[PDB]
Amino acid sequence: ARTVVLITGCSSGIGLHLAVRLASDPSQSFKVYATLRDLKTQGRLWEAARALACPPGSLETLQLDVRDSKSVAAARERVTEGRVDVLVCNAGLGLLGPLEALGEDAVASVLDVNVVGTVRMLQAFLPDMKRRGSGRVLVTGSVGGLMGLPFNDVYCASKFALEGLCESLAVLLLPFGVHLSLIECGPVHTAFMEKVLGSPEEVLDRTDIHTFHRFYQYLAHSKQVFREAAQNPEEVAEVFLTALRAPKPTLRYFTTERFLPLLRMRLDDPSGSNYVTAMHREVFG
Amino acid sequence: ARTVVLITGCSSGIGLHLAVRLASDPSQSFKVYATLRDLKTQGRLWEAARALACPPGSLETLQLDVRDSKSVAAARERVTEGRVDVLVCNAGLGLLGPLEALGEDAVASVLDVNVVGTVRMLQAFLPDMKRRGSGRVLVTGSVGGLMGLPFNDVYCASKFALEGLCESLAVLLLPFGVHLSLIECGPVHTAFMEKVLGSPEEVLDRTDIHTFHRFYQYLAHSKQVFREAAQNPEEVAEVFLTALRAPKPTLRYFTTERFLPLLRMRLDDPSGSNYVTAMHREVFG
Ligand SMILES: NC(=O)c1ccc[n+]([C@@H]2O[C@H](COP(=O)([O-])OP(=O)(O)OC[C@H]3O[C@@H](n4cnc5c(N)ncnc54)[C@H](OP(=O)(O)O)[C@@H]3O)[C@@H](O)[C@H]2O)c1
Ligand SMILES: NC(=O)c1ccc[n+]([C@@H]2O[C@H](COP(=O)([O-])OP(=O)(O)OC[C@H]3O[C@@H](n4cnc5c(N)ncnc54)[C@H](OP(=O)(O)O)[C@@H]3O)[C@@H](O)[C@H]2O)c1
Ligand SMILES: C[C@]12CC[C@@H]3c4ccc(O)cc4CC[C@H]3[C@@H]1CC[C@@H]2O
Ligand SMILES: C[C@]12CC[C@@H]3c4ccc(O)cc4CC[C@H]3[C@@H]1CC[C@@H]2O
C-alpha cells in the first residue's frame, strides 16, 4: 500500500534528511528503510526522526555496507514488503587533495563505494523492478559529476562515472517501466573539510611546494563558494521528491541553476579549452 | 635528445600501432617504451616493429601491470633516460552485457585497470614532469566516455571517469607547463566481441528473457556501426601524433566527427531526455 523506499548512506547529509522527509510525510504513504554503513552512527537519524515526529513503523534502520554484496543481499532480504518501490543510491565518499598525495587505498575506496557500490545496489534491486515493470531509482549526483574541479580528480572520476553508469542504463530501462534519475546537487550544508583530505603536513610531505600553494588557493575559493552558494539539505531533499512524483521523470534533475552557465561553456566547447581556462581563472585567478 | 615516450597496453590495438608508428618515425626522434601486462603477448608488437623496420634501440618492451604500483614503479625505474617526455595512458578493458550479468570481479577489474590504473601512472609520472615544468600526457578516451551506451554501463562508467579525472587535472596543470589530452576514438578496427561479454547461455542464465532479447538487438546494431564506421588504428594513431605536436594542445581530440551531432543533442538537453530517447531508437528502433 505504502511506497517502500530504500535509501543508502543515511548517517548524515542528504540521505539522513531525505529519509526523515519521507517517513514523516503528512500523507504517511512512505515506508522507509534508511541504511547506514555503521549502526553506531544512527543517532542523528533517530534524533531527526523524533523532531519531525515520524510515526512508529514509517522508518527502519538497516546496516548495509555497499562495498559488500553479502551485506547488500542481507538488507535486500530485510525488506519485509518483498519489494522496493523507490531505491535511492546516495552513499558516497569525497576525496580532496593533489593526485600524488592520495593513497592508493583511498582512491580504490572512493570508486568502490561511489561506483561499484552503486553497481551492486542496482544488480540486487533492478531485477525485481524490471520484472514487475515498475520502480524508481534516484541516484545522487554532483556538479562535480558534470565538470572537473581541481584537486577533486578522483572524486570527479567517480561522480562522472555515475553519470555514465546511469545514462547507459537509462537508455535500456526506458521500455521496462523502470525510471532512473540523477539528482545533481551543488554544495549542500552539513559537511567537513569539503569531503576529506589530509593535514597540511601530510599533504606537504606528499607534493611539491607550488602544487601545495595551489591547493590552498583552491580551498580558500571552495570555502567561499560554499559560504555564498550552499543549499540546505531540506531544499535538496525536496528535489528528490519532485523527481519521484514526476509521472515521466527525466534522466537528470538539478537542485540549482547556479552552475548551468559554466556547464554551458563546457558543453559548447567539446575540445575543453574554454572550460579549462574559465575554471582555471575561476579558482586560481 | 630523443623524445622519450612510454605507452601502456601495447599488445594490440591503438597502443601497439602507436608504439610502432613512433619508433619507426622517419625522423628517429622518438625513443619508445611499449609496456604490456604479459610479455608473452609481445610478438604482435615485434612483428609490426619489423614490418615498419624500427631501427635498433628505437623500441623497448617492458612488463607493466597497471593494477600494481610496484609494477608501475619498476617500469618507471627502467626508463634509462631518467625522464619520460610523453606518457600515453592507453591500457583499457571493455565489458559488455546486462548489468545483472556482470561479475563483481569483472566490474572491479575494469575500473581498476581503466581508472585506478591511470591514476597510478599519473601519480608515478606527473611529479617529475611538473618539476621540469614540461611533459605531455595523452589518454585514450572513447565516444563511450562522452555518452552512455546500453549494455556498456560499467565500461562507460570507467570512460566517463577518465574524462572527470583528466579534466580536473587539466585545470590544475595548465600553469605547470604539463599538457594532458584525451584522444576520443569511435570504433577502431582490430577487436573481438566488441570488448568482452559472456556466452549467450551465460548471459541468459544471468538475465531476464526480454533484457536478453534487447542485448541481441544492441549487438546486431553495434556490429553494423563497426562495419560502417570503424577506423584503421593507423588513422587513429595519427591523431595521437597531431596532439603531441600541437604547440598548445587542447584537452580533447576527436578521431572522427561522426558522433558529434549525437554528442550535440546530449549537450543541448541537460536533462538527458532527448539523448536517452534518441539513443534508444538508435539502438532498439
Ligand atoms: N555534501 C555535499 O555538499 C553534497 C553536494 C552535492 C552532492 N552531494 C551528494 O550526496 C551524496 C551524499 O552526501 P551528503 O553528505 O549530503 O549525504 P549522506 O546521506 O551523508 O551521504 C554520504 C553518506 O555515505 C554513507 N557511506 C559511506 N560509506 C558507506 C558504505 N561503505 N556503505 C554505505 N554507505 C556509506 C554514509 O553513512 P552511512 O553510514 O549511512 O552509510 C554517509 O551518510 C553523495 O553521493 C554526494 O554526491 C553532497
Ligand atoms: N578498440 C576499439 O574499438 C577502441 C575504440 C575507441 C577507443 N579505444 C581505446 O583505446 C584503448 C585501447 O584499445 P585498443 O584495443 O584499440 O588498444 P590497446 O593498445 O590494445 O589497449 C587495450 C590494451 O590494454 C592492455 N591491458 C589490459 N590489461 C592491462 C593491465 N593490467 N595493465 C596494463 N595494460 C593492460 C592490453 O595489453 P598489454 O599487455 O599491453 O597490457 C591491451 O593492449 C582503450 O583505453 C579504449 O578506450 C579502442
Ligand atoms: C563538488 C561540489 C559541487 C561543485 C562545487 C564547486 C563548483 C564550482 C567551483 O568554482 C568550485 C566548487 C567548489 C566546491 C564544489 C562542491 C563540493 C561538494 C559538491 O558536491
Ligand atoms: C564505445 C565505442 C564507441 C561508440 C560506439 C557506438 C556509438 C554509437 C552507437 O549508436 C553504437 C555504438 C556501438 C559501438 C561503440 C564502440 C565500441 C568500442 C568504442 O570505444
Image: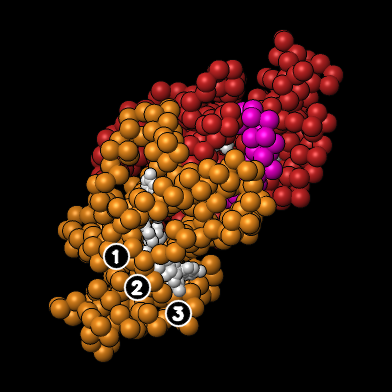
Chain colours: A orange, B red
Q: Is residue B28 left or right of residue B90?
A: right
Q: How many marks?
A: 3
Crowding near pointer 3: few (<14 within 10 Å), some, many (20+)? few
Label 1 near ligand 1 (CB < 8 Å): yes
Determine which residue is flagged by label 1: A233
Specify whether residue A39 is in view: yes
Determine which residue is flagged by label 3: A41
Query: Which of the pair B170/A108 is nearer the observer?
Result: B170
In the rendered image, the residue lying farthest to the left is: A27
Q: Which residue corresponds to the image point at 52% horizontal and 38% vertical from the top-left? A: B172
Mark 1 or 3, nearer chain start:
3
Label 2 near ligand 1 (CB < 8 Å): yes
Mark 2 or 1, nearer chain start:
2
Mark 3 or 2, nearer chain start:
2
Q: Which residues are magenta?
A: B111-138
Q: Is residue A141 above or below residue B262?
A: below
Point out residue B233 in the picture as x, y percentages from the top left corner: 59, 24
